[PDB]
Length: 150
Length: 144
Length: 216
Image 1 (cartoon, rainbow over the protein chains, first blue to last red):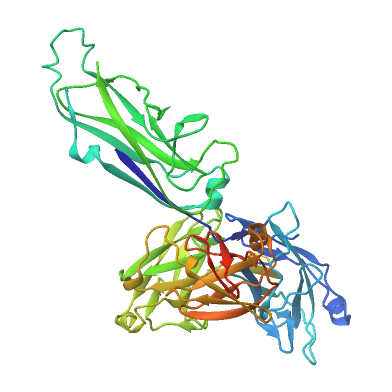
Image 2 (tube, rainbow over the protein chains, first blue to last red):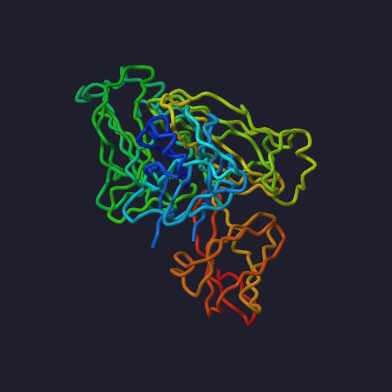
């Protein structure tokens, strides 16, 4: 006789984006425009959930807590501080709600029926820091997309 | 009669390890694993008691619980959606006791080589669920 | 780009070490994978009793590797008749971007890591969650977990279908502990939980007044 053995488990989600380095480019922006109170065009920040059963992020409770984390503009958890000393900050919108990066729970069910991509939009703007001023120069930032399973 | 299964091949185990429910449910197939039947102390030479004996050939047959409509899928004990599929010479094996193809045997020992995999069964409604699974198959030989 | 192989990890106390599989699902670029351990309050711990190694590693495109979980002599100071809670973390470091003015996303997977002493070692598909006791109270039920294991409850309703699809607030009971959850009273209570494999079985109760035990 031959006895076959195996085990089956629920796998955690894996993510990916249109870009291999998981980034979105805001292109060039006018220092004066942002300085005057103008904002960048909201960019599509789409995260594809793969290698898992998405029947936990769907819409229509959740066993997977979802949250974003990154340095924030003091006093503004919804403003993701950036690198480059440009004075700019990044804001991310989920599904009618803003994301916070102080490590606060986000909406883990923002999945539109028939899809495995969570949709967000991100805009660049002058920091809300008192006496902040937009300056020429390239900026960048990294946000941690945290999935904590129960 | 001509041969005898090796002590190690008569009772063997194959462990495919831990698999992803997602992978399986989406049609994923596990890595293959070797399943070898070792025939030892074969005396085909002495298999000369009536040369009708078409060479020292042997046909192997497998038996075990089967998935409805698919006799080439060994059913897993417990659970519901999984299935084991075994291959030889690129040909699938059926678990209803049907004799396989003829294998030429030389004196001494010969090794029948097969490979196995785990996957979702082809049965309708088949749903992969998590947990520990095991499937058992028995085999018998007939010599020609 | 980097992924873990399970949603929870059970560490067999009879073992001194075990491994977890990780993967760089990105076929084009290399990503780094950091791993560390947190205590029950999710605070990072570096000095044991459970250790994660390597703390960081490079994964070429499509590369499969693993993280090792090891224990220190202090592991024996943990209670040996119940489980102890830890958390395992896997977070990637995407390659620095080429473009300027960019935002990058980095995935961090956090899962429960249950230290299971040898004395309570378990068998392949064993169930202990069927020892859960339900006591009806003012506001809902008081879940009682007398087993030496952590039990994660994800549902509680009057039907099997309601236990699963029902809107419930997931709560985890510690070994030998109870807890009250707000809920409507039900004739035939049904509970849903997450087992070692990530499965979500459904338990059916039968009540004898304010007490409800699982139906065998």
